[PDB]
Image (cartoon, helix red, strand yellow):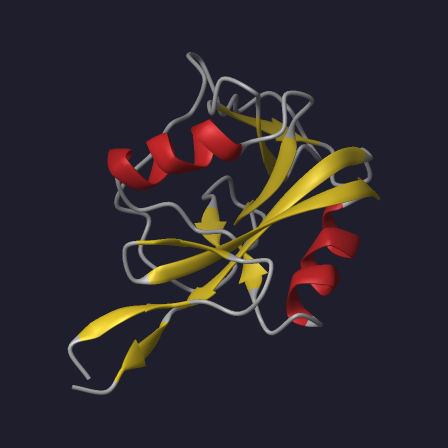
Length: 135
């Protein structure tokens, strides 16, 4: 009903969402399926507060997030279909002169870099909606 902050075991709540901080070497598409199979999707980020929460729990060696140049025209969009209403790109990113670097990762600093999708990273972040306590 009113309060939406219930998360499944091993997921961390932040506002109306649950986040899973995944570990293990995976290319972007593998991380995408690892999230799907846990009933989540690679994370989408919509505010500086959500980014600050992610930065605090983010792996120091980089993590895949759910942003990708899906339409192959240079427009990076969230795989969950949510609005691109916030960005935390590292300065000068994304570059127009980086053909094939269609996937996005988050650095230890929390800043985003585009990357080749077949790059193997040690971390990945899933999100899903929190469920609600009945009033």
